[PDB]
Amino acid sequence: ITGTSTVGVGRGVLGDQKNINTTYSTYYYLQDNTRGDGIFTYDAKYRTTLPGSLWADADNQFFASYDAPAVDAHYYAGVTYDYYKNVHNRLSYDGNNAAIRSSVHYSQGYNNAFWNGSEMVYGDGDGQTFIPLSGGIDVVAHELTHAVTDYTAGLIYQNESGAINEAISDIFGTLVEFYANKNPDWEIGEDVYTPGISGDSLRSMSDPAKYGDPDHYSKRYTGTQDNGGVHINSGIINKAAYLISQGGTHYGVSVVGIGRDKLGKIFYRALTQYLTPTSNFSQLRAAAVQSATDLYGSTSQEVASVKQAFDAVGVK
Ligand SMILES: CCC(=O)Oc1c(C)cccc1C(=O)O
Ligand SMILES: [Ca+2]
Ligand SMILES: [Ca+2]
Ligand SMILES: [Ca+2]
Ligand SMILES: [Zn+2]
């Protein structure tokens, strides 16, 4: 809507207070005009029609229970925008400052979040397996990264290209988490997963196996569940990414870590310049090696570490 840019304050899912960019026109709307062509957060009001209504609030204060998932969807999308802009010189998910839209309070007891081709969508969780999913910045950044991927590589969402698609979202969701720097980890979803159990997570990049995901190509899933295992076989790439960044010896293969920033540079380059809708794990390895080579030279440590990492996960 048309209005004047304002700053409101609220409490997120985890009870943390934050300021948020809003727009004033009779009501205060969750519309951030400070980034690209705007960030817009909607109320789906527990139904599944999208996007629902642009979030309207009478006084610019957002401390109601009902407001918290909105506060975080809105804020963490702003942080994710900032990451891609400042760190990769990318303007929004299409690179041309497309409006970023999110809807929260989707459906009832809904344990998922997704990119629907046009916007981000967050369920509130059933309060057992999940709390409102926008409460985790790695979740928000995972979702917005699905938009980035669809506008760039276009990785089809099934089988190996689908596993790569998922891994890219976990990788950048994690790099954004570290970018915001509030107790970052190499785990996925820990902030909104199983409120009753501390210490766990939906996935682990450091040790995928912890939650039944493969950490070696020889262990990949080839059945048909989960689109040919997109959230399962992503463990193999997540592990490889972890290794490139943090190093380690995995099944006897030693990897010298090169750090998170170089990991991000390499995978961002592979994503936007070399992967295609049907890339498989072997072609991602070549893409990662060629990207590292572009960035640091064929005789670099960086290239050598990428190869070590894919060797360690059994991807040639
Ligand atoms: C880290 C965010 C995530 O994985 O969200 C999903 C959930 C919670 C359920 C089903 C699919 C997804 C997804 O984004 O792929
Ligand atoms: Ca209010
Ligand atoms: Ca995390
Ligand atoms: Ca938990
Ligand atoms: Zn995903």
Image (spheres, rainbow, N blue to C red):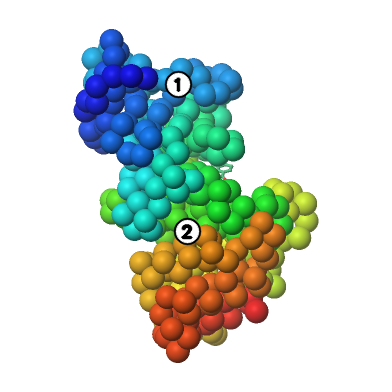
The amino acid type, in three-letter code, at marker 2 is Ile
Please name whichever residue, 179 or 124, is drawn nearer the observer in this view of the structure: 179
Residue 154 in view of the camera: yes
Q: Residue at the spot x=24%, y=22% of the render?
A: 4
Question: Nearer the N terminus, badge 2 or badge 1?
Answer: 1
Tell me, yes or no, whether the two marked residues, 2 and 1, touch with CB atoms within 8 Å: no
- 233 vs 137: above or below: below
Q: CA distance from mark 2 to mark 1?
A: 28 Å
Q: Residue at the spot x=44%, y=52% of the render?
A: 173
Indicate the quadrant where residue 233 lies.
bottom right
Tell me where residue 235 appears, x and y as whole percent.
58, 62
Q: Residue at the spot x=63%, y=55% of the render?
A: 155
- The mark found on residue 43 in the picture is 1
- The mark found on residue 20 in the picture is none
The amino acid type, in three-letter code, at marker 1 is Asp
Q: Is residue 203 left or right of residue 67?
A: right
Indicate the quadrant where residue 216 lies.
bottom right
Tell me where residue 23 appears, x and y as whole percent.
29, 23
- 12 vs 84: above or below: above
Please name whichever residue, 147 or 186, is drawn nearer the observer in this view of the structure: 147
Q: Is residue 177 left or right of residue 307?
A: left
